[PDB]
Amino acid sequence: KTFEELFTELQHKAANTSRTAELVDKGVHAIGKKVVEEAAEVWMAAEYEGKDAAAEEISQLLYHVQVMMVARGISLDDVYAHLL
Amino acid sequence: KTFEELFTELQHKAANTSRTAELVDKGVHAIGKKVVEEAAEVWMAAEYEGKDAAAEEISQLLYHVQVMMVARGISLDDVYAHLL
Amino acid sequence: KTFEELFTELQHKAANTSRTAELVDKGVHAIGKKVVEEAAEVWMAAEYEGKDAAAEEISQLLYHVQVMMVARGISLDDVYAHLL
Amino acid sequence: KTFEELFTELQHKAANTSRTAELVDKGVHAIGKKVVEEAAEVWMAAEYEGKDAAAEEISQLLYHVQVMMVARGISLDDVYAHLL
């Protein structure tokens, strides 16, 4: 249920394709389009929709950011080190 | 050092202003501009820069996403419930 | 060759589908994804690529902005009135 | 009143500062933030607001795209050549 647990789950699913979202294969460009569209959706939901809708969009944004981390070999420690 | 720990730290700093980034006062629009500009920076860094640069940009994005959550009263449980 | 001429060409192609890009049918959400992704690409090219590459990305952005105008029934006069 | 005329007006105002918006001085990064935030505003207005509000946001996006062209030395011919 932790951010760290779900991330390790994604690193394993990326070790290989046709089941769960394999954007890692498509690459940075494809993942970047999603990050960018989701950020706009997060802003949109935060402004016009309810808390639940905003939380759903935020989860999609986080998911794609995590996928981008997996695609570039970035770890939670690398990111956390900067969150300070 | 956990995503959950840093988030609770921000919820407290939002209980009041002029010290650490108080975007919560400015509102959703101000935070949204940041989320959107940071997403594009994340994509840019992921494509042209190194792993560390990408991780720094990602941390900035996550920070602003967390701020947006604080501003809208969204909790980690709300978001995590959707990450599944 | 004028912005105004190409726009009127697009308004006609939207009067009906399967030839040239018919995003008007898919709707605002689909065109919005493109505008938001191209905006980031424009920023990216402007920063890391040459003038021609940046011009190509800018043309893609303008095209999708124009499509959004068509999809929402917005005219050049409506927009131009605000450009002042 | 034409896209081409307003653009030539901006090229002259960029020949020098403190009157009309001088982004050109601040550079690509500052203009890029605007392009990226305006694209999200364009999408937002297109989805939730009226035609006029969408037109106003579109005008702001075009203005900044034009400024970006000025800042990078890109001409209308360069862009128009690609719009085909």
Image (spheres, coloured by chain):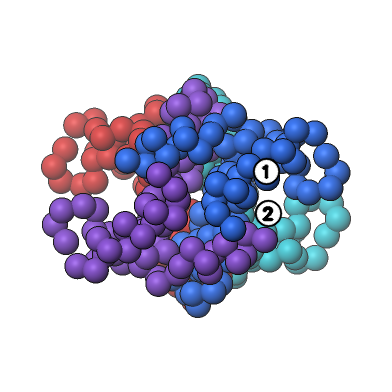
Chain colours: A red, B cyan, C purple, D blue
Residue A13 vertical position relative to residue C33 in the rendered view, above or below: above
Query: Depth check: B72 or C66 in front?
Result: C66
Query: Depth check: B51 or D84 in front?
Result: D84
Q: Position of residue D20 (x, y in %)?
A: 78, 49
Task: Please state which amino acid type lies under the numbered disc 2.
Answer: Glu
Query: Depth check: A3 or D33 in front?
Result: D33
Tell me the residue that label 2 is attached to.
Answer: B9
Q: Position of residue A3 (x, y in %)?
A: 45, 48
Label 2 residue SS: helix
Task: Please state which amino acid type lies under the numbered disc 1.
Answer: Leu
The chain letter under disc 2 is B
Q: How many neighbours does mark 2 have within 10 angstroms: few (below 14), some (14-19), or many (20 or more)?
A: few
The residue positioned 50% from the left and 77% from the top of the image is: D50
Q: Position of residue A8 (x, y in %)?
A: 36, 39
Tell me the residue that label 1 is attached to.
Answer: D10
Q: Position of residue B4 (x, y in %)?
A: 55, 52
The residue positioned 48% from the left and 45% from the top of the image is: C39
Q: Quadrant of the N terminus of chain C?
A: top left
Q: How many neighbours does mark 1 have within 10 angstroms: few (below 14), some (14-19), or many (20 or more)?
A: some
Q: In the visual, does D66 lie left or right of C38?
A: right
Q: Can residue A70 be seen at all in this image of the molecule? A: no
The residue positioned 59% from the left and 58% from the top of the image is: D1
In this rendering, which labeled residue sits more in front, label 2 or label 1?
1
Label 1 residue SS: helix
Q: In the visual, does A22 lie left or right of C6?
A: left
Residue B66 occupies quadrant? bottom right
Same chain, labels 2 and 1: no
